[PDB]
Image (cartoon, rainbow over all chains, first blue to last red; front, side, top):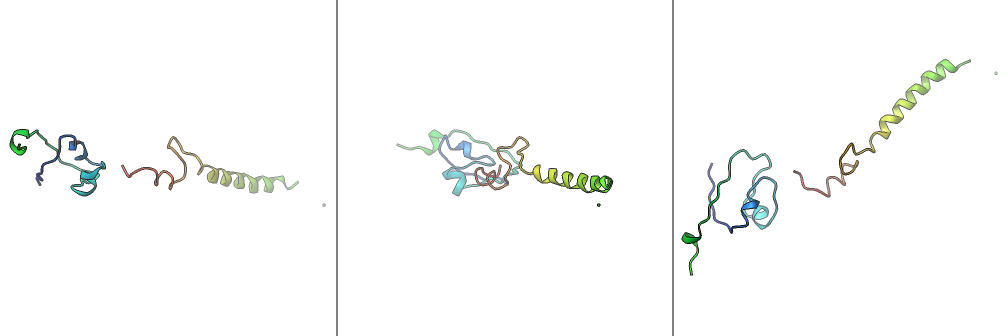
Length: 50
Length: 45
């Protein structure tokens, strides 16, 4: 399965098994025996607009 | 009005059963030895 979304820059540390915070609490929660991989890259020029 | 053999038997057993119960208040290198306080002061992982 591939899940996709957009978050802040310093919220990428809550996408991991066993974390807390406004993102992992109630936006997107990863089980505690996760198996896959997590990939993330900056996208300032595409998503941020004056 | 002697019976130390039987007595010995009886005792050897009560003293070995007392140690098993006393071994429940030891952390063995955890924070505490009571399964709730460890459980209501940390999160599962």
